[PDB]
Image (cartoon, rainbow over all chains, first blue to last red; front, side, top):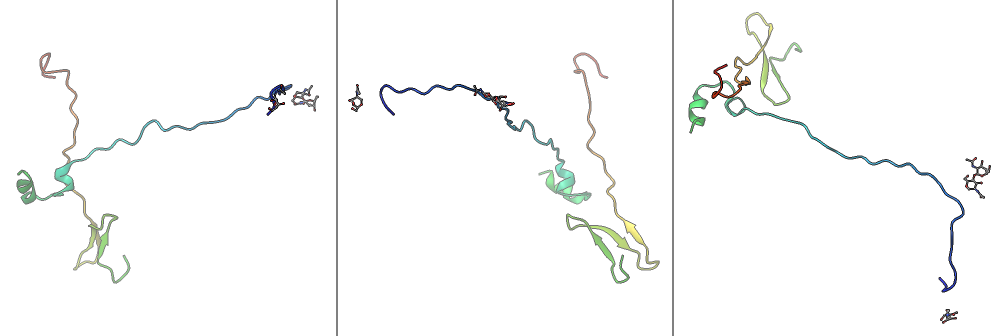
Length: 49
Length: 49
Ligand SMILES: *[C@@H]1O[C@H](CO)[C@@H](O[C@@H]2O[C@H](CO)[C@@H](O)[C@H](O)[C@H]2NC(C)=O)[C@H](O)[C@H]1NC(C)=O
């Protein structure tokens, strides 16, 4: 730093860079009566509470 | 199966295969249910199709 000195460029360069971004995630679906009680009929009537 | 094994388990640690105690053959176990159907409708105010 001085108070009557300046620096100027005489040349240049072209630069290419990258940038990654997420957008979406996985879609899922569920069914309780299959997950909780599998294939029982007795558990279905209790889950119906 | 190896000659001394009687059961088979899946990644969820639930039984999926068995050995018949009399013929010594392997049987898969599969669910019998299909509740997840999707219904496309154009609105009951227009039609019942
Ligand atoms: C400004 O910068 C460019 C960037 O390289 C300089 O170009 C190089 O200059 C000399 C001239 O042929 C060679 O060493 C290289 O071949 C040039 N670049 C390439 C890609 O070949 C240029 O000389 C600079 N200008 C000044 C006045 O310094």
